[PDB]
Amino acid sequence: VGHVVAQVQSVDGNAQCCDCREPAPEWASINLGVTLCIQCSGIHRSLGVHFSKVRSLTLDSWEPELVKLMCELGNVIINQIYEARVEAMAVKKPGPSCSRQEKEAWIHAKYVEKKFLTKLPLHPGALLFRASGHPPSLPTMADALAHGADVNWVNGGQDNATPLIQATAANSLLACEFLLQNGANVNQADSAGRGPLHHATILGHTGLACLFLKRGADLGARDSEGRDPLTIAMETANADIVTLLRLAKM
Ligand SMILES: [Zn+2]
Image 1 (cartoon, helix red, strand yellow):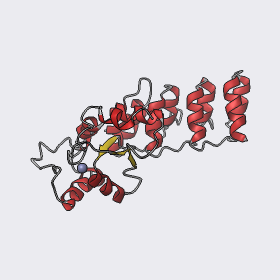
Image 2: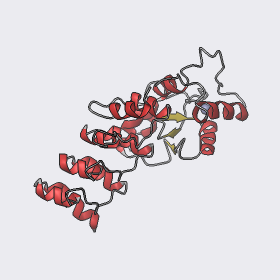
Image 3: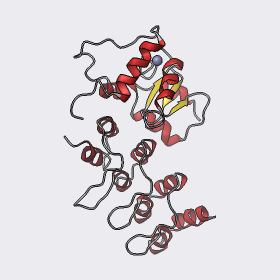
Image 4: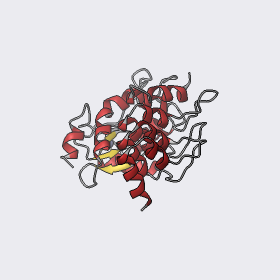
């Protein structure tokens, strides 16, 4: 709520549109972590939610975690990834005055075709998994995802844990939020049937528990020990999480 557009635009390179450098962009992509002008945000709407989730900095409400998330990413960071090879390819980015068509071609090459990426972010999924854990590196998570990292990557042969479960073990609201904006299944369990909600409640992370409930975590899911999150909350003597879970059931 605290002027979102002022705060988000005050971040490194966020006062130029990410795709065409149009000044004072008032739009955003919340899974990418970037600001966009009227023209480029309109084009992002073309791509679909898998590539880009468009929001207004001035006209839409913003959850505080999400503002903070925007502040750890930003145009400079994201362009270091998505436009990494532009200089080496000798190709020319659009400016503010360019044709809709020219911006369309650039945006599609950049985000769909992934044409300007470096070759390596060798294992994008494992990199995402590592970068989501304590202490998380959101630029590294962004780089891994741009290189095709599965947001629901399973750490096989080991514990079958996911990046979301790692971000949960790290107590990282930001990394959790980032993964969820990028399609993480809030219900995907590890080998012991313990989903992100189970982990939040094992570790006494009330904020993360509340985050997962807001995003449709299954209240009734039972782990390999037959425990749902309420049972873990009782057994850990955690009055706040018991309260949450009981309220969520109502
Ligand atoms: Zn633009």
